[PDB]
Image (cartoon, rainbow, N blue to C red):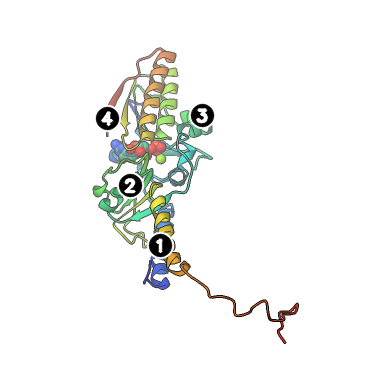
């Protein structure tokens, strides 16, 4: 296992990743399209889901069956860090699905999540994603530990 | 608008169309095809809203965009990402970052704001304007017929 694996999801995750490219192979990014992919990302892992080119209910059934495939690209590690926005459609779905998988690995990890504040859509998503993490904490019987950063 | 050439109006429309062509060119950071779809088809995910005729306002300043009344759905493009400000009270809001090497980038920031509480007035102005014009032309009073029941008129209206 590596010391730490860093996982980023959705646009916000992609954007934060650009600041951590010096960590290279330890960084793993996921999104549903390439709107946020920039040149510096060549230095890290980037995986885009298939058939997915803001609505979480729409994105979920498309990405769910692909999660096992995403997880195979994430090495076993002694610790993980997960990072995404609570308020969009892709990060707030990929992030928690991967988080659920990390719980199944009996992993130690923390997340960095952003409270998006632009619109009632963002705010509704923030609520549903926090509730998602709570449901996961209960279902997997594990604390889901997050550093919460409001915009 | 009275006094303005169709040439002038057409030029303005073409320049606005180009901004929309730019908007949807899929080359902006952070901006998805799905982001655009959910901006303009806002009732798809906001089911409590009423589908109806809405106006699109295309503005090149924050100030002008903020002055769109009762904004529903907003998309902002910025060339300088330092200038991004989450202004207004729309229900849906998204931002894209334009590229300085994008030759189609005509302005430093462009805001595409959709509302619907503006169409009313527009229609009123047209109805009121037409009414006034019709009133001036309506208030007419034709003269009495130049032919009396005395003239012998045949089926083709021939009087011989
Ligand atoms: N802190 C932060 N917030 C962002 C950033 N980009 C977008 N946001 C906010 O997060 C929301 C979700 O955007 P994004 O993460 O790109 O959505 P996703 O790709 O569907 O996961 C947006 O509506 C913004 O309010 C970013 O780079 N940093
Ligand atoms: Mg996105």
| Quadrant in which residue B132 is drawn | bottom left
Question: Ligand 1 near label 4 (Cβ, under 8 Å)?
Answer: yes
Q: Evaluate whether label 1 is on the same chain as label 2.
A: yes
Q: Position of residue B141 (x, y in %)?
A: 50, 71
Q: Evaluate whether label 2 is on the same chain as label 4.
A: no
Chain of the residue under the numbered disc 1 shown in the image: B
Of B16 and B140, nearer the camera is B140
Mark 3 vs mark 1, CA separation in Å? 58 Å
Which type of secondary structure does the marked residue at label 3 adopt? helix
Report the mark closest to the observer, 1 or 2. 1
Q: Residue furthest front?
A: B150
Q: Which residue is under mark 3?
A: A64
Q: Which residue is under mark 1?
A: B129
Q: Position of residue A95 (x, y in %)?
A: 40, 29
Mark 4 vs mark 3, CA separation in Å? 26 Å
Mark 1 or mark 2, earlier in chain: 2
| Quadrant in which residue A104 is drawn | top left
Question: Ligand 1 near label 3 (Cβ, under 8 Å)?
Answer: no
Mark 4 or mark 3, earlier in chain: 3
Q: Which residue is under mark 2?
A: B69
Q: Residue at x 42, y 28 (%)?
A: A75
Mark 3 vs mark 2, CA separation in Å? 40 Å
Of A59 and A66, nearer the camera is A59
Labelled disc at residue A149: 4
Mark 1 vs mark 2, CA separation in Å? 23 Å
Which type of secondary structure does the marked residue at label 2 adopt? loop
């Amino acid at each position: 296992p590596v010391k730490v694996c860093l996982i980023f999801a959705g646009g916000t995750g992609m954007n934060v990743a650009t600041k951590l490219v010096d960590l290279g192979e330890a960084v793993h990014c996921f999104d549903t399209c390439d709107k946020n992919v920039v040149d510096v990302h060549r230095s890290v892992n980037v995986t885009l889901t298939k058939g997915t080119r803001g609505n979480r209910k729409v994105i979920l059934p498309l990405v769910r069956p692909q999660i096992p495939a995403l997880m195979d690209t994430i090495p076993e590690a002694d610790f993980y860090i997960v990072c995404y926005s609570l308020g969009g459609g892709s990060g707030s779905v990929l992030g928690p699905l991967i988080t659920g998988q990390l719980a199944d690995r009996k992993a130690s990890f923390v997340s960095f999540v952003v409270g998006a504040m632009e619109s009632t859509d963002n705010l509704g998503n923030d609520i549903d994603t926090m509730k998602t993490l709570e449901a996961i904490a209960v279902n997997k019987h594990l604390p889901i530990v997050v550093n919460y950063v409001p915009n | 608008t009275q006094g303005r050439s169709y040439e002038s109006i057409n030029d303005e429309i073409a320049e606005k169309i180009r901004k929309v062509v730019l908007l949807v060119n899929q080359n902006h950071g952070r901006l998805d095809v799905h982001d655009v779809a959910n901006w303009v088809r806002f009732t798809d995910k906001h089911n409590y809203l009423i589908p109806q005729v809405c106006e699109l306002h295309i503005e090149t300043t924050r100030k002008d965009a903020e002055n769109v009344p009762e904004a529903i759905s907003q998309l902002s493009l910025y060339l300088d990402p330092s200038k991004e400000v989450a202004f207004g009270t729309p229900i849906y809001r998204k931002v894209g970052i334009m590229k300085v090497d994008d030759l189609d980038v005509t302005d430093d920031q462009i805001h595409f704001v959709i509302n619907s509480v503006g169409v009313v007035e527009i229609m009123k102005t047209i109805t009121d304007s037409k009414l006034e014009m019709t009133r001036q032309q309506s208030k007419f009073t034709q003269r009495n017929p130049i032919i009396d029941a005395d003239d012998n008129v045949d089926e083709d209206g021939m009087v011989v």
